[PDB]
Image (cartoon, rainbow, N blue to C red; front, side, top):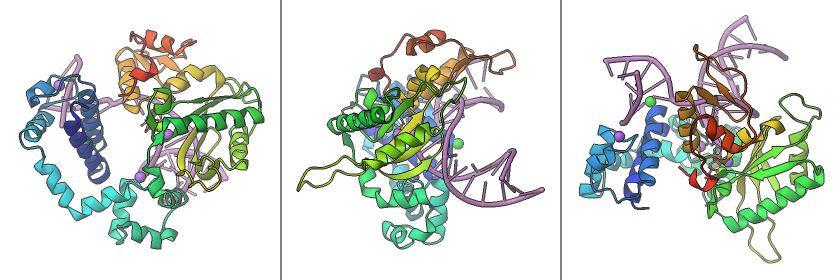
Length: 326
DNA sequence: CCGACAGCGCATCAGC
DNA sequence: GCTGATGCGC
DNA sequence: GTCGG
Ligand SMILES: Cc1cn([C@H]2C[C@H](O)[C@@H](COP(=O)(O)CP(=O)(O)NP(=O)(O)O)O2)c(=O)[nH]c1=O
Ligand SMILES: [Cl-]
Ligand SMILES: [Mg+2]
Ligand code: NA
Ligand code: NA
Ligand code: NA
């Protein structure tokens, strides 16, 4: 946290560009800069010093100089005072409300929590659950609670079918002392890249987690991806735990290593690694790593029997999950 | 200068 | 209904 | 907004 002031400023710029400007590449440019500065192991003394880092160009360098000189950024000061921008930024904090819906709601005069609450019938299902748990979803999850949640999910999954394997990924697998949500990778031998010998593989697990009242709400659900809400049980006379976001991703069992590389992240780590793969003439998704032909067209899946195999292909030294928090 | 920026699941809608 | 684009999310 | 070619 040597450069917390700078990385906070860049993140706020990132969020502005995403939510208000709807300029997604600016968003990702700012997040990449924040990431590389966050892991830079010196307290930055100037914009020129920061500009040496990949992802920091002239414009961000000038902003860092302004920020270092004054402790603030005029551009941000004004954005903060703009009502429309402030409203749009707020609304997008609701899960299921993105840049477009936020701006549309503001047009219709819906721009506070109070407005949303009295206009529940103007929300889709995802948005309505996002609003319901607005407070809860912004709270952090202590790793100690993540461990309890892990135990429940792994044990309930076992009770459905002992051949299921559930792996908690995301920030939890990277060793984080707190997480924003729980991400669960799921495999079953019936579901491979070659065949699906059993239906409802994901459904069965979701149903069981609902039965024991762990899963409380659903944001979206298909054959391979569940996005919803869960809650730890609490003891007698205890205040309830907050509700938590949970993502579950069923991946073909022979593609587990690509799947667990993907779901472990971070998102910026994946973007960096996938970008590097492309420069090395490969393409990586959660399923496979494939070569790129001269045309750029993806070839056939390369054999993969470990996370490290994927790193090897693109000539990266292996990085343990705890070192992937970019 | 300027094209590219990771890659994809689910919900929703327009157009047929 | 299907298909493709878009929004939002991982 | 940044970067590689
Ligand atoms: C948001 C996002 C996630 N992912 C993958 C990598 C994440 O580590 C993983 C879980 O996504 P989350 O949105 O839950 C972020 P996290 O890394 O789990 N940290 P936390 O949930 O604690 O905030 O999905 C991507 O590949 N691209 C993405 O844009
Ligand atoms: Cl952009
Ligand atoms: Mg997570
Ligand atoms: Na740079
Ligand atoms: Na949102
Ligand atoms: Na998640």
